[PDB]
Image 1: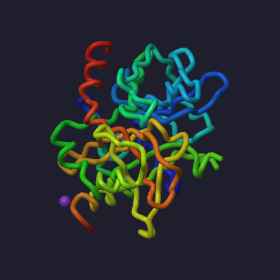
Image 2: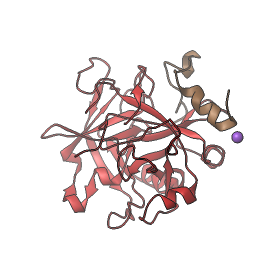
Image 3: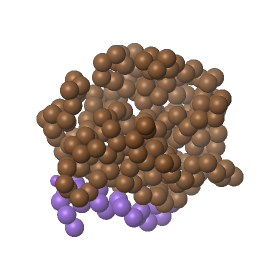
Image 4: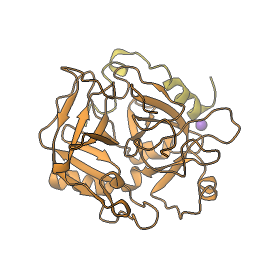
Length: 31
Length: 252
Ligand SMILES: [K+]
């Protein structure tokens, strides 16, 4: 549980998937 | 999933496929929440109007999968189930209230690049993220359209949470605080939904505070697939978290 929600091929490598920005944008508005 | 796109490899490493053993049949989605525990919708396992009642021996899960039909060696893992737990107040007679179940794997699954658990929300994460307009992500291998047409690669779609009064107005079914709904407005140009076979899979949100993905919802029910003004309904994971904990703490 301590390591939950951090994906080996993305977060752990400082890589972003192609659509996760869309989520962040929705939480703040735009950009 | 309607109007989704193909997942990147490792994009949803908590994705679980729930299968009927014989005949081989993909039943539902599910999610990995620890090395031994899998979360799904109660209606995937128990639905009396369809004379549906699966026990642990009827079922198997597949974890780490990307392709729907293709065997992915040294990557995907097949587990049997030790035990199924359905919420004791699951309401199939009326409205799918408390549409939640837990499945305990016979043996813990080894985590890898492709297999890794999702977080359950705490009260602060629920407060921050579960707001109308904020988007989550739904994933699955379910139908691409209305049941009455199957993807080869896990599908992904991002959908905004809908205001509770709008959810209420979309349906004659009595909705409860154990559900929320998500989907785009008619004539937004944007579309997307979960469909038959995506049930039980995860609705996840990524926290800007700690960069972790949290499972806020379980695909539960909907009037149609990507129908105008018909958002999908999701089991409200945070509202049912005390039950989840009681089961894991007691039977883990
Ligand atoms: K905001």
